[PDB]
Image (spheres, coloured by chain):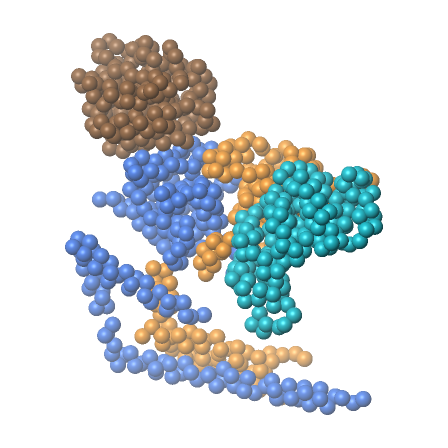
């Protein structure tokens, strides 16, 4: 569907919000997110703290004002027209039924169904400390995957930060970790049919056929250059370097 | 070891000065001769420090504090005087980038030695705690100081300083590692 | 007079759905509000009020903190008319509301229509009343109930909130007949008289 | 004289992201931070003046908007000192404007001191950052001293930049690049489809080389160059093609 761009600026700021707000896990610092949502890839330009109150002692009890967004967008629009409201964020890390109320408030203010944003203010788990949800509805809400863009100007300052293969595997466990547990969770949580829906694609393995072995067929030619890869290495430098040395070492006139 | 005080006398505090920093200048300037021998005047000036320690945020004073906060540990260096540490520790904590800096030195100078890990904690705390470039900076130097020949000892704070996000701790870490391992090469170091 | 923040609690509910005097209760609520709020902003300019939904199956703010018409603006649109008590929650929201009340030295105030049969528990009710008095909220209530809503929480509550009256709570329980709310409460120290504490 | 400017890169990127579109005009607006003793210039935040169709101008600064935000920001808990000026000066090592100075200058009145932060949104793009801060006048100096008391101070006069963030965002920032498992091996298992081309690629890699090698017998299409380069890329994918099984 509309799965979205992610703005580090947002992400950072939202955490400084979290920081600034002195928010603890008792709370989730919330606020507007900005972008333009029309495309099958929504973009997140920006995002804004909505000064807020959250109480899960009584869930539906919590406080927020729109008049921010009122005053906000005006300036924001005046700042940039592309800022048009795409949705909103919060801290998280995880959902609370208070959300849905919060959710639909923005539906007043959004073109499409507005966007939740989970953050992990502790940035703990994985790729993203983040989720973004959109109500669907029997309610639905849903996370489409998202990611960062360039934002190179960001990436440039980002370049001032940091400083091939393996990781690709490294999630090998993750879902599989919780997964069977997740079963045994629900298994011994209730001790749904979706799970059985998950099931049949398990057989989708031990599948391997001679069809497999055709791999090496391919893998054969794959290796042809392995010499040639280094054959030119196998050729040039120290030939010439010796020459160059023979030049240089014989240079040595006076 | 006599004249220098009288040398500083016209520029000593109470002899006034044209500049309070000129006036502050003698303070540090004094111990230059008297290092280790000026403790009295030092502590005396430290009294003037202690006098203005818990107060007197005049830059002019802060210099008069700092320049004194300078020369204090200067003569107090290697001599363990908690007051030197302490009196500075306020002047330190008084958070004058002017003044509090010298504290981050003299306190190191006082306990220069194996010192005490508490000041280290303090310093290292004040490091992460206190918000300043310099005031935060000179701490590790003081940390570098009172970790002296301790070698294996400071490795924690070293490691801590090493593990620091901030240059400053890493920075002084080497100096710490130095005063620990200076002279004899510790290869690993 | 008043420098304090207020909240308007509207139930649009089994009573508000149903005209208690023209044109509906829920409508009778309306201009009484502005009437009130006028005198509220006449109490002082900067006197702020909230507006929430105690109505329907969803509690929520309708008009947030402000100080002029933007409420009268906000209140302009409807509600669930037959809706049901969020009061406790709504109040507990109205409390948290006032916890964010703008440019404090504004004391906390709340004004509450009762358009609902009023289902809640006394302790919770008084925990509110406590929490209010704790938070130090001014609490005055608009109630015309069946019978009325009274000999009940609402009666304990205004008491239970209240060590000092208008620093905590005053009550009026709205009567039937050609009783114009704004005309009625013109009497009660929900408005006028002494206005804040 | 040697002075310390500090940014939360948020405010940086905010400027940037705002300055990145800023062209033609400089992006303008508040800068949020403080002064810790001397030397210490922090920026926690910053934000746009809403565009001035007249362009960057001292009039264009609106203190309502700030108040608006700063309120909502104070509402956010967001609060700082307005620490100076920041703008986007495309293609400009330059200097900003005597105006821009006068802009800051009439403004830095509002402070003990302020900044006018140059950004070349153009040449910031290098992957390094182009950026600067003027504030042209001194006490004496780090204490420069003469040109003020002797009057007529007109110069570039930068301040000295820095900034600080955290390892916190840093990790999350390094988190840029369900996810990878969905995203990698296994999403790019897409490899065997084109083996015929993966041959043919390699098969075309072939011819290019004797040709290239031939020249071994300056100016170029070098006999030795592409040869390796040509194939070598394939290898990694050519390699990993296996892995998923």
Name which residue lies at 58% across and 64% down.
B150
Instruction: Decide which of C174, B100 is in the foreground and name it.
Output: B100
Residue D31 visible to an observer of this rendering: no
Give the colour chain A carries in the figure: blue
Question: Along the horizontal axis of the image, is A197 left or right of D92?
Answer: left
Vertical order, D195 against B130 (above or below) = below
The C terminus of chain A is located in which quarter?
bottom right
Give the colour chain B carries in the figure: cyan
Vertical order, A23 against D127 (above or below) = above
Chain seen in orange:
D
Instruction: Decide which of A128, A224 is in the foreground and name it.
Output: A128
Residue A16 pos. (x, y %): 47, 46
Question: Along the horizontal axis of the image, is C64 left or right of D109?
Answer: left
Question: Along the horizontal axis of the image, is D135 left or right of D44?
Answer: right
Vertical order, D10 against B173 (above or below) = above
Name which residue lies at 63% across and 58% down.
B112
Residue C58 pos. (x, y %): 27, 33
Name which residue lies at 67% across and 39% down.
B51
Chain seen in brown:
C
């Amino acid at each position: 569907h509309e799965k979205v761009t992610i703005a580090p600026l947002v992400l950072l700021s939202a955490l400084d919000h979290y920081e600034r707000t002195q928010t603890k896990e008792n709370k989730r610092c919330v606020g507007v997110i900005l972008g333009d949502a029309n495309s099958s890839t929504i973009r997140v330009t920006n995002s804004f703290a909505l000064p807020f109150e959250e109480d899960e002692k009584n869930s539906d009890v919590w406080f927020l004002d729109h008049n921010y967004i009122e005053n906000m967008n005006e300036m924001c629009k005046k700042i940039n027209a592309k800022e048009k409201l795409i949705g909103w964020y919060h801290s998280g890390p995880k959902l609370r039924a208070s959300d849905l109320k919060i959710n639909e408030l923005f539906k007043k203010y959004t073109q499409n169904n507005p966007l939740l944003l989970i953050v992990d203010v502790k940035q703990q788990g994985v790729g993203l400390p983040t989720d973004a949800y959109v109500a669907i509805e029997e309610k639905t809400f849903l996370h489409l995957p998202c990611t960062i863009e360039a934002e190179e100007a960001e990436e440039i300052g980002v370049e001032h930060l940091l400083r091939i293969r393996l990781t690709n595997q490294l999630k090998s466990l993750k879902g599989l970790q919780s997964k069977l547990k997740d079963v045994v969770e629900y298994l011994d949580k209730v001790i749904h049919t979706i799970l059985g829906k998950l099931q049949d694609v398990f057989n989708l393995n031990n599948l391997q056929k001679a069809l497999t072995v055709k791999t090496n067929d391919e893998l054969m030619v794959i290796y042809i250059s392995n010499l040639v890869r280094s054959i030119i290495a196998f050729d040039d430098l120290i030939e010439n370097k010796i020459q160059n040395k023979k030049i240089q070492e014989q240079r040595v006139k006076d | 070891l006599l004249e220098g005080k009288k040398v500083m006398a016209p520029y000593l505090p109470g002899s006034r000065a044209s500049s309070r920093f000129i006036k502050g200048g003698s303070l540090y300037g004094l111990g230059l001769i008297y290092a280790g021998f000026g403790r009295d005047t030092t502590d005396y000036l430290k009294n003037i420090i202690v006098e203005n320690s818990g107060t007197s945020g005049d830059e002019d004073v802060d210099v008069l504090l700092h320049g004194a906060s300078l020369g204090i540990g200067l003569a107090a260096m290697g001599s363990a005087n908690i007051e030197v540490y302490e009196a500075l520790k306020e002047v330190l904590y008084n958070d004058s980038a002017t003044s509090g800096e010298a504290a981050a030195l003299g306190m190191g100078l006082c306990m220069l030695g194996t010192g005490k890990p508490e000041a280290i904690h303090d310093m290292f705390t004040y490091s992460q705690e206190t918000q300043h470039g310099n005031i935060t900076r000179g701490l590790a130097v003081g940390l570098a100081l009172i970790n002296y020949g301790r070698q294996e000892l400071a490795d924690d704070l070293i490691t801590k300083m090493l593990a620091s996000d901030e240059s400053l701790l890493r920075y002084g870490g080497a100096f710490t590692i130095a005063l620990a391992y200076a002279g004899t090469g510790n290869n690993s170091a | 007079m008043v420098l304090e923040a207020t909240v308007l609690v509207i139930d649009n509910s089994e009573y508000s759905r149903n005209g208690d005097f023209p044109r509906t209760r829920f409508e009778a609520q309306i201009d009484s509000v502005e009437f009130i709020f006028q005198a509220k902003r006449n109490s002082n300019p900067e006197n702020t009020v909230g507006l929430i939904s105690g109505a329907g199956a969803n509690p929520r703010v309708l008009s947030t903190f402000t100080a002029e018409f933007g409420k009268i603006l906000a209140g302009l649109h409807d509600t669930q008319i037959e809706g049901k008590l969020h009061m406790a929650t709504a109040l507990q929201i109205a409390q948290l509301t006032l916890k964010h009340r703008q440019n404090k030295v504004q004391h906390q105030r709340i004004v509450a229509f009762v358009c609902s049969p009023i289902s809640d528990s006394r302790d919770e009710l008084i925990r509110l009343a406590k929490t209010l008095k704790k938070n130090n909220v001014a609490v005055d209530i608009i109630n015309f109930g069946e019978i009325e809503q009274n000999t009940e929480l609402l009666d304990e509550f205004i008491a239970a909130v209240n060590n000092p009256q208008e620093e905590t709570s005053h009550l009026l329980t709205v009567t039937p007949g050609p009783r114009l709310l704004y005309e009625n409460i013109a009497s009660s120290p929900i408005i006028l008289e002494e206005g804040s504490s | 004289t040697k002075e310390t400017v500090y940014i939360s890169s948020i405010a940086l990127l905010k400027m940037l992201k705002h300055g990145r579109a800023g062209v033609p005009m400089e992006v303008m607006g508040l800068m949020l931070g403080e002064f810790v003793d001397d030397y210490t210039v922090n920026v926690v935040d910053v934000f746009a003046m809403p565009q001035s169709g007249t362009g960057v101008s001292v009039e264009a600064v609106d203190d309502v908007f700030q108040a608006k935000m700063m309120d909502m920001l104070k509402q956010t808990g967001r609060d700082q000192m307005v620490v100076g000026w920041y703008h986007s000066h495309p293609g400009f090592g330059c200097w900003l404007s005597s105006v821009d100075v006068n802009t800051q200058k009439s403004f830095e009145q509002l402070n003990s001191r302020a900044v006018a932060v140059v950004v070349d949104p153009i040449q910031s793009v290098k992957g390094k950052v182009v950026i600067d801060a003027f504030r042209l006048i001194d006490t004496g100096a780090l204490i420069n001293i003469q040109a003020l008391i002797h009057g007529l101070n007109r110069h570039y006069y930068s301040l000295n930049i820095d900034y600080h963030k955290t390892a916190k965002e840093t990790k999350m920032l390094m988190n840029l690049h369900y996810e990878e498992k969905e995203e990698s091996n296994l999403a790019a298992t897409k490899s065997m489809v084109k083996i015929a081309e993966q041959y043919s690629k390699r098969i075309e890699e072939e011819k290019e080389l004797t040709e290239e090698e031939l020249k071994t017998r300056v100016g170029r299409q070098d006999p030795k160059k592409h040869l390796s380069e040509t194939a070598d890329e394939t290898l990694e994918n050519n390699i990993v093609s296996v892995l998923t099984a």
